Amino acid sequence: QNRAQKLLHYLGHVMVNGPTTPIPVKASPSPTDPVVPAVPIGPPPAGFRDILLREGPEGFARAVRNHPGLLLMDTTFRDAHQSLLATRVRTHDLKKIAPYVAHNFSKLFSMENWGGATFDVAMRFLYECPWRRLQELRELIPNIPFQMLLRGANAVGYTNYPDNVVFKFCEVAKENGMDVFRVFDSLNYLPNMLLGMEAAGSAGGVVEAAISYTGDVADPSRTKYSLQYYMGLAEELVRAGTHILCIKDMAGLLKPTACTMLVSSLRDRFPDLPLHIHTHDTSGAGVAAMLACAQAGADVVDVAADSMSGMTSQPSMGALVACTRGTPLDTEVPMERVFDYSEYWEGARGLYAAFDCTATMKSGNSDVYENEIPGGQYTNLHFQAHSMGLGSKFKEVKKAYVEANQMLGDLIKVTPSSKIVGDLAQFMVQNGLSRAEAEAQAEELSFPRSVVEFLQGYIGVPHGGFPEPFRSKVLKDLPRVEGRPGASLPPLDLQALEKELVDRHGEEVTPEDVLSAAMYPDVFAHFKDFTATFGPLDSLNTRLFLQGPKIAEEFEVELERGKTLHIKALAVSDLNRAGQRQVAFELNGQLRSILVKDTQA
Amino acid sequence: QNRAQKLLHYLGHVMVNGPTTPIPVKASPSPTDPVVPAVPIGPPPAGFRDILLREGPEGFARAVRNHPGLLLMDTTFRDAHQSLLATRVRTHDLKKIAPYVAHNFSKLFSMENWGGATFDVAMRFLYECPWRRLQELRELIPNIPFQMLLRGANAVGYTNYPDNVVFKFCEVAKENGMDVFRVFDSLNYLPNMLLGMEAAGSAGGVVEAAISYTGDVADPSRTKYSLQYYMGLAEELVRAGTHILCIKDMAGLLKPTACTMLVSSLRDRFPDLPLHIHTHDTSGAGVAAMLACAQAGADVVDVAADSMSGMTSQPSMGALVACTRGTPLDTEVPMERVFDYSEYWEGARGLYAAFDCTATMKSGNSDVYENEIPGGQYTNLHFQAHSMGLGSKFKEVKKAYVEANQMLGDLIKVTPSSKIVGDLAQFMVQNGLSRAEAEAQAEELSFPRSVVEFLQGYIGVPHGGFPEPFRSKVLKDLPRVEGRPGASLPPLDLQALEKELVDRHGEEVTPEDVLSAAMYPDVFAHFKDFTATFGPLDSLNTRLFLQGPKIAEEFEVELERGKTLHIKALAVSDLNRAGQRQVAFELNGQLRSILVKDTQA
Ligand SMILES: [Mn+2]
Ligand SMILES: [Mn+2]
């Protein structure tokens, strides 16, 4: 077995040289293994994915809109760990509790488990294939709809790609098993949001236009992104044609009062339009928030498993289900099941001890109502300062964030945008620049590549326009983008890229691989060469994958399905073998050894 | 200076032999120092403590009941850290942010900062005087009311004390600066609750009778502790005379729905009675819950600073303040201030890294709706299991907890009671006893000392009676307590105890000390001998206290107020000096050395 030995070499390697992917927090994966509940044999109870197929996104939206109780979505597979564990959860652990979900959470609206950071991190850090993840799970959960976070601007990539790809991406994603597409734009720049809605709607999937939330519509003071701001935007999005409408409060800024307001005026304007609410518990509301949303007529709300909820993540699924039963919005989900599910996750999370923000973050923070830093980014900046004894610092950067944000014309901060305000915020602090010093001396300073490209609109056009008195003194003799960036981009010959990959990585390369390579040229490449020589490192349980094997400890890995592979380390030490070393394993009935390179560790 | 050298010897000792008080989690106190905001010079803005004094608990309650916005209480000084940090926060760090509080949180209803575990821990583990704490803080915050958790049954002790002490306790406490007394009974056994109310009322303080909450009044299924159960209990407590009425949801089981119900029928029955709600965010509601209580007419709700809220503690103060502004329930508290306040606590908590439940607990858990384990006990049992790689176990015990509780007739689990179900739950588990095996074999097994005395009523009589078919087969030829246990207890000759202490510890012993010794004979004794030889270990900053000083690191300690004491370690090594060693400090302008005992460390 070449599949076999490829992995051995790997295990051996991690033993000799240690961890392959970065480990931000010095900690070994919990020695305990996640508790996987029991599940009856045979097919799931069948939930919405069934209806969808049976009637399209058409009847779907209706059933959704006409469902009595509150409906939910599980972000535990995507945004939940993307916010708490540096989006490091591996397919392996996701496949584990999959059969459970399929059997227990059929009443489920959708299940977020793809899109977002994941596509990137899957190759850049976990060395697994994002497509495999999908197919492997779609296989395990045929009854629950699959949702992803798609960026209208550029699918799951980091830069503008020709529009021919956005459609081909969704085309594939759709066939591979994706259903609901949540398209968003960091500036709510419709052009990008509609392109996303296109590829998604044309791919034949469910379009769920997502509006990113800033400030507080309840507060009449601020008028930039006023209630009427959103309301207008919806019209366009609804006209452009969307099955479901979602409100992406990525910063956990939605207050109950603001909620009641927003949703009602929305339910009023669109009586039978499905409404989906996404918030992060960063401020401390979330639950109280979501509850208000239902009250006012919201159809669904995003939640995460208790053990993976709270703080920069989504509100406690169990708290929502609990507070909602006995009422006309009852979710009808057995508390018992949320327990076993959270149970699993509390243990699963134990493996990702090396990526637990829990190291620096011991709770939420209402100051988010001031800096407007989204959940994910919050956690990271927090960890950064504190991880280097600089909590004192964090206060300061947060203030530079506000100024930076105001300095660019008060913005909507999400992946694209949010990270540009970040660099500028840091640029100012690390250079001691008051907003005034920053603006006045703006005629010439080396502002972040991200900031300059933003003002050139590479992403889009901020509502209210660019801070021109400043924008120009910055841009100078620089090319300012005109129109939807992706527009002026010539297509991407897929055959040129296709044989260009077959020619190299193999006669294997699949449509999927092509796309991946497309979005992530290098990262994909590296990911391919790595797995090339190390086998299916994705079938390895997280512990072995991170920490590597323990000398003498018996263990097994399910390669494919006909093999179980029982291995036990025991023996390494050839300290000098021509500048190397050699380890031996007792693979199944026999035994063998692979040679590693000490890398003078 | 004897004050001086006494501390030196201590510091040195810690250097040579290490930590004096147990340290559950191996971690050193953060090297960063909590950020203490700025506070104007001169007197605070004055709040309710002022009104109180000017009009007695009579005008106070009215003002409370007639105040427009929602009122709050800060448990950050007591229940917040008692649930999260093993009640280990020191007076030193409480004095620091005190002036700030006095200046910024005048609108505050009360401030919980005393009572509960504190009195015990203050001597048992921190080696500080609980009275000192009170006096020192009363000094720093003369404008905000001081609240404490007083146990009707036995003030701040662990056993039945003759009622003469219960009155003498509140008498002293009241004069020392305590105002509002929250009196509670673990089984809501009126006899004990009234005794507390008396001492509290008689002492001339504000009586806030507390009803302990269980189950879910919204849920018609369970009828033991039905709505009409509480409603009736209210009548008694109000007739017995109480200025304010509080609901102690020590387990965080209060759902919004159950809330709206409870409070309203309460505000209905008592139009102008002040209502105070206490909850723990354990389930995930809390905030959502409290918001409901207000909606329905609740006058005050307990909260903690953001960095100290969440999980088994109280809801995010900032989340409440945030979601409540702009509405008729506006707290009027400047978001800005809750920020600086949490800012301070996030850092102060970094000093207590050795007691942070954060180590095992990374979030709340809605399964609380099933085991009914109060916030504090949850945290402990969770740390327990997991701190010894036994999370797998924790599930099990939670199950025994339910059976144990059901086995004792379904109870209200708070400090007294709650820990009895604990022992029983663990007894069963650790002896493999189904609730059936536990009961049938009850005729004779060595049930916990706590469980036996419970059935003998040493605490009180459980509503619905004791589980007799069992109770008896357990008790056998054992004495069953008749009436409020404290009643049958002969007074406590205070002079006998007074001269008894003077005679020993010194001609210093104060009325306070007497009471302390009373409730905590030994603990007090040890606490006294320790401080006796080591000086004011309470004027030491938590870092030096826990971790001791760092060789060559310059530092200072504010002994009293006329001395600043600048010390620098540097030099220890007399490894063998007659089985000891010797360290040297460079105290202020001069230098000197103290001789320690290596304890063959
Ligand atoms: Mn999000
Ligand atoms: Mn409590």
Image (tube, coloured by chain):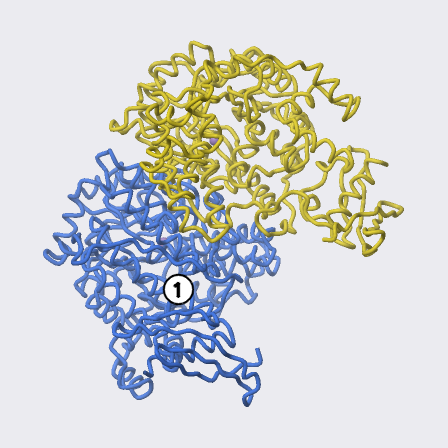
Chain colours: A yellow, B blue
Q: Quadrant of residue B128?
A: bottom left
Determine whether the beta carbon of the residue marked 1 sits less than 8 angstroms from the nearest atom of ligand 2: no
Is residue B426 visible in this depiction of the protein? yes
Residue kind at label 1, given as amino acid type: Gly
The spot of residue B458 in percent (x, y) is 39, 66
Q: At which x and y percent is residue A53?
A: 59, 14
Residue located at (51% from left, 77% from top): B16
Secondary element under disc 1, as helix, strand or loop, is: loop
Furthest toward the bottom, the residue is B578
Q: Which residue is mark 1?
A: B457
Near-viewer residue (B323 or A484): A484
**Relative to the observer, which residue lies in front, B309 or B83?**
B309
Residue at the location (42% across, 73% down)? Answer: B568
Q: Nearer the viewer, residue B34 or A472?
A: A472
- In the figure, is residue B149 to the left or right of A559? left
Name the residue at 63% across, 21% down: A177
Of B482 and B70, the residue lying toward us: B70
Q: Position of residue A127 (x, y in %)?
A: 68, 35
Q: Is residue A43 visible?
A: no
Which residue, as the protein is rendered here, is positioned at the far left?
B54
Which quadrant of the figure has residue B413? Answer: bottom left
Q: Where residue A22 sits in the image (x, y, percent)? A: 62, 44
Q: Is residue B418 above or below residue B516?
A: above
Label 1: few (<14), some (14–19) or many (≥20) C-alpha neighbours in 10 Å: some
**Residue A445 sits in quarter:** top left
